[PDB]
Length: 129
Length: 259
Ligand SMILES: [Cl-]
Ligand SMILES: [Cl-]
Ligand SMILES: [Cl-]
Ligand SMILES: [Cl-]
Ligand SMILES: [Cl-]
Ligand SMILES: [Cl-]
Ligand SMILES: [Cl-]
Ligand SMILES: [Cl-]
Image (cartoon, rainbow over all chains, first blue to last red):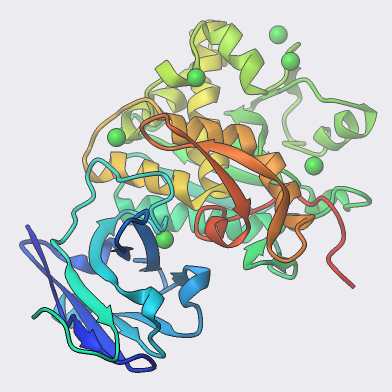
């Protein structure tokens, strides 16, 4: 069982990025998949989730209208399209499996599986690779 | 005389249970009153009797079946049928006592318990709190059997009350809360039984207050926070509707929608 995240990097304010979460060893089709983010000195927070039922999607207020989550079942992969990026979006982004979408508010579930994360930095000026 | 939704524990899967709960929800609400992306149940006031109840038929591999009756106004169990016998919780007023005479009308062997179906009473009768009653497909199969065997003289009251606690959580509370449906799905997926953690218990205890806070909210904010618990028992406060949208699947009607 592995969840592999890619797509992070440094992007300019107002720019866009697409993160990928690819599963191995199991099928993402029968789980909800959530994106979470941890910014420096801040509580880790749910960002977006997509249900295993009927493609229902949920978003944190702070990203509504800017981020879009989607799933490609044939590729066993979930994506987070991030547009209109703001400095406040800088964080490590994680994906995780859950049975149903919760945006993390009840804590980690005992059987939830998390990836290792990708750094997203929103800034006009260069930085650490 | 009312819509019936069927489910069996025999060979149950995540998918069969999910499809069952979806059907329950679809019969509890018309979908015409949705607020903050959460459906609202029908208003009880003036609700015609033909619209008041739905039936949930549960079967197990031993070929026992019981049919629960749910009140559409609160998604809660009011009684059940086993064969041609029916049993009802104590009703709260004359109108509700009259309403339940319209359930299982081909059954003359009918009994109304001296107690209601609230958790406080059922836990007292069961001799155990919800935190010590295991849930899962096995518990549900056993609860079906116990409800059935009350009608043959084979279930004593503590076991009956425990079995009601199981059914109410796995059917009524799962219909109300997608999060609770998810907790039951986990138990099916991993073929396990376990008691509900504090997040489940506190949500159950908070459904009426959450329904109020959402319907009385202003700019998506609650007038006063509601305290919930995480799975590890730690306490946190909720101030706004948005984070509850994925959690809550149905709300009891509290007031008319905004103009
Ligand atoms: Cl979900
Ligand atoms: Cl069974
Ligand atoms: Cl109805
Ligand atoms: Cl009510
Ligand atoms: Cl009695
Ligand atoms: Cl009572
Ligand atoms: Cl308890
Ligand atoms: Cl469990």
